[PDB]
Length: 179
Image (cartoon, rainbow, N blue to C red):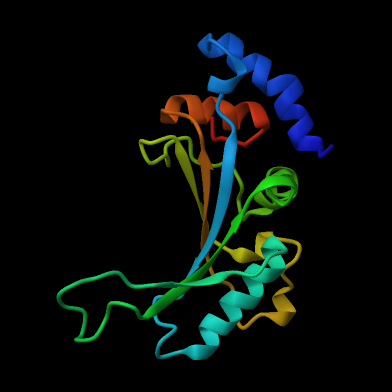
């Protein structure tokens, strides 16, 4: 099976069982999905920036993204709800583990003046948000084939009830948290 899923089952689960003393394996947190988002605030006025985001996400995630849109509202330069504002791709299963394994071992360390990732960016519901400054850290991206360096966000959704349990799950999986 996938290297990281094996580490999860053989090392992480028993470690979480010991760390939180769950009643059974069914209560142990797992990563459920990883949502890779590339905001293109404009996109409406710059169709090409959205197109680039869509292609780069396809390269980064090995899966086709979906366009994200603005939610209901009042003001926003008149006209707003429904306008494209970026693109996202949600990974599950084997592809999700492959992506995270590479993210942890290859991409994140390649970040400019890398000093580890934030231990604080959790949403209070057990999910981790990783703000990425430059999409260039992904080996699937080639600077010479992109219109420009840009950032993105990666949300790692877990089945943990709390940030504390999700953080331990991610640390045990190898997430290079700042220290």
